Length: 265
Ligand SMILES: CNc1cc2c(cn1)cc(-c1ccc(-c3ncccc3F)cc1Cl)c(=O)n2C[C@H]1OC[C@H](N)CO1
Image (cartoon, rainbow, N blue to C red; front, side):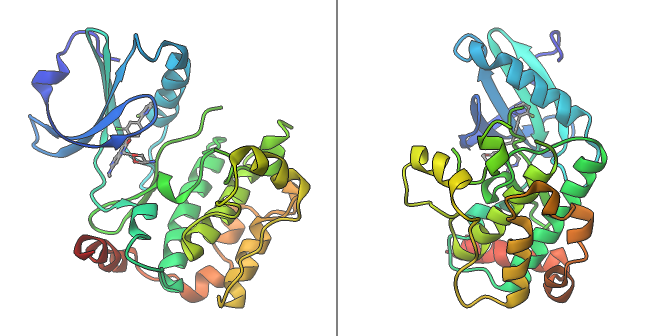
């Protein structure tokens, strides 16, 4: 964290993207390069109880160097406000891109494959994302797919063993299975229910299945991820060779059509 430089001289703050975790996020410009950045501004007096979680996400992101994890550029302290600088991904989140209408299975498989490449990276680095969901998957304007918003070390994407506070990288594989349902259907299982009910339903019930006129390989991909027994879930490495992925995923550049569809909607 840079406690001497003035982030307001280094960056031009533009429109708010939204309210992410801990603080508000803005599109911005690096005044030296003119590249577009994402800027999170956290009021450290308002958000004092969460400061250690902020620090640990900074540490984790600063240790990542992968095409599949959103790039971290640094942090700055100005008066009471912490500025966190990340690369700007102009395609939006996968959740955003569901808005115009359903994805097809080529788009689903392509997005899951890229998520799996990021999970393979993280798990090989002995890291766990802990919040895989469509809202935390960001696309560049070119269709590149990257992970953002790591979870801290809402229940709908949580593995049962995380809820029972009993976990390792296989929790991410469960969340990936929920995310696969989300990309196919628009919403995770139990999305109509109160979160406190979902908290006991996930451990209690059989795992969700993908319901609808979807290919059997896609239903099998979901079922493989959504086993109650973590040791029965496959690794990310193994899932990159799943027949659903191999038979349906195509070049990421094709996802620009999905980004364009969202702009015309
Ligand atoms: C739309 N394009 C876009 C959005 C971004 C970011 C990059 N491109 C980067 C971020 C981003 C994340 C974490 C952090 C961060 N937090 C704590 C500690 C360390 C950190 F680096 C900082 C930033 Cl700038 C971002 O919030 N959005 C918006 C966000 O997206 C995903 C949603 N689920 C919610 O909205």
